[PDB]
Length: 215
Length: 212
Length: 194
Image 1 (cartoon, rainbow over the protein chains, first blue to last red):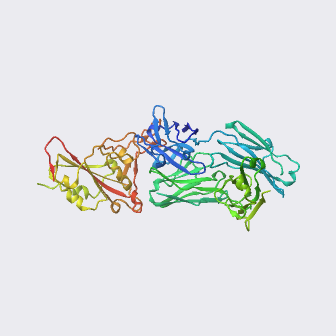
Image 2: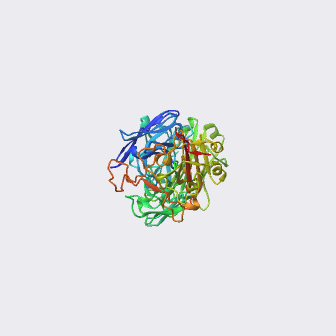
Image 3: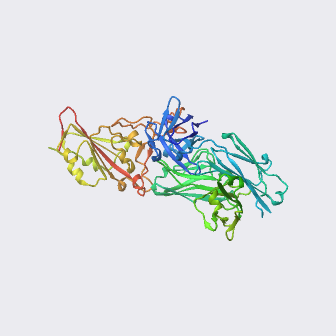
């Protein structure tokens, strides 16, 4: 099958460097307009750079003097060298083949994720979101101040799934992530059923089981 | 060249005819315009290029047309796998221009959220920070306004919020908003309130507690 | 003792496609470049290594007038040291270019309702043109490991694209007529003088 496979993304400090690779099969990188396009969390696509079949290159302004596109024809591979990285550059990076008016960007890689941050790996603190003291009751867990993504939350070791909403994390100004997970239940069950959220943060190897009861 | 895509989001049902428009700011060759589809966590996928040419492999219910400044993507009989975001793109230029995108989402009847407010836990308070959390549960449509109030003062710049994807069963949304304060700032005030404005509510609903 | 026929280049009824750009060789005549600049109906008139008033007091072995049509936004590529589709694959000026680049909007002439498909440019080429190189082949362009053998398909594209000029396009997409004056200084008798 025709494909492009990116690799090289990962965590990197602001000011640091990172090289992405895009190994191609079914198209010849050296004979195509080849582009890098990125997508920051929650935003749209942004074109980053291009290398023409003849070897000319171009770059988005926000990346000029920091990024270099290149290629190894013998390895049919496209590269993006990224220097002087910034928190902004955090994104999923796609390589794509560009046919211009003869066809769109018809072949895309699966993406590789680049996270630029000065935070250190840190497991979350898990705080109860305690059902009110006054039909349907709501309770949850606030999974606060962890890095990096991701975190996973189950309820009662997976026995409780219905009515659960685990929300996308927000990046706080501190550089740490925070998310909430909630469940709605019959208020009559608060006196009889136990409610435990199970939080997993693999990067810090942290596992937390927090019991949430009325306060 | 700027591309203005409208509407930002559209509600539709299976079997509907869906029309998405892309307005260019000057007048461009039809060969310059492509349409892409994207689903969450996935790479974009080319649907149409040169404004009307169907990409091989793409179902025939997708069709493009337009010229000059005004281009259109039409899905003639919406299928469940079509709920997704769609982007128009202006090719042949470096940098290319992208439209803002249109999210095609599942239409259903209006549903008011149930609203809950959660004070900070004692455990968190020992640590010097207070997070107050407001939950808006299973509402529709997605548009919703959360206003935090502290002793009836309207709060700005000290909250963050997050929204789920459309529920697989009832096609509603849920929203979580966190107001963050230092412990001392928290202790300077009494009434903590979350005020929710939504189409399904005749008047805004406020959930509050008194610190203590 | 005879006028250089600059009018039959600048005032020609039809212009070449940029990929098949036209070249008029100019010899054994007197050229007045002051009337050229003083026409002042040109959106671009840029000289490299010379000055119009100054070059009217000069002689050269030969003068070349190259003419073609591109899009407005591409006119900046007709200059030394530029890269891009036109400079790379259609018409390349040398780094040491000595001469002038003249352009004007030709929307009233070269665009038509429904599109003028006569004007084309080369979109796909494996390597850049050398300066003053002209490539007119129309071989199907092979973008992958499978050979094309003259039939279009996946990874197999016709190398030229039409401008499709329409009069209501944005100015950057409207046709511009371009004449490039190159001044050839050979170790030979000079035949073109002011």
